[PDB]
Image: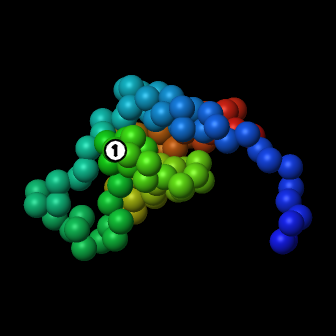
Amino acid sequence: SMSVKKPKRDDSKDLALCSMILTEMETHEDAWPFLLPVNLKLVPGYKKVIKKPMDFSTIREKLSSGQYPNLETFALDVRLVFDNCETFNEDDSDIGRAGHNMRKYFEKKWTDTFK
């Protein structure tokens, strides 16, 4: 509350560490469905169904331009990429499987770097 603060967590490395995680996501062999925005002219249904499209390149630009106020807003966009994928793709599809694999990979790196 006013003039009453928990001890200050060092957040000065968070930008660099989110960039490293994002690099590791970008270079995973199963990243290919997620590297670029889904083409809303060429993929019927996507525009109407997925209210908030997200992809790695869009996260990378937001990161590089100071559009994430903190590390939690960064994790929310990464998770949004996988939530969108599960909304639109069957579990038993190459893209459906890619999304589950990448979410697992991300959540481990996140825990090991920050928890």
* Residue 101 appears anywhere in the view: no
Residue annotated with mark 1:
61
Indicate the colouring scheme. rainbow
Q: What amino acid does circle 1 point to?
A: Glu
**Extreme-left residue of the structure:** 41
Could you say where residue 94 lies in the image, as x and y percent from the top left?
Answer: 33, 41
Which class describes the residues within 10 Å of circle 1: few (<14), some (14-19), or many (20+)?
few
The quadrant in which residue 48 appears is bottom left
* Residue 15 appears anywhere in the view: yes
**Extreme-front residue of the structure:** 3
Q: Is 87 placed left or right of 12 in the picture?
A: left
The quadrant in which residue 49 appears is bottom left
Q: Assign a secondary structure to mark 1.
A: helix
Could you say where residue 96 lies in the image, as x and y percent from the top left?
Answer: 39, 48
Q: Is 90 placed left or right of 110 in the picture?
A: left
Residue at the spot x=67%, y=33% of the render? 113
Which quadrant does the C terminus fall into? Answer: top right
Count the labels in the image: 1
Residue at the spot x=35%, y=55% of the render? 54
Which quadrant does the N terminus fall into? Answer: bottom right
Could you say where residue 9 lies in the image, as x and y percent from the top left?
Answer: 77, 44
Relative to 54, residue 29 above or below: above
Could you say where residue 60 lies in the image, as x and y percent from the top left?
Answer: 37, 41
Residue at the spot x=22%, y=68% of the render? 47
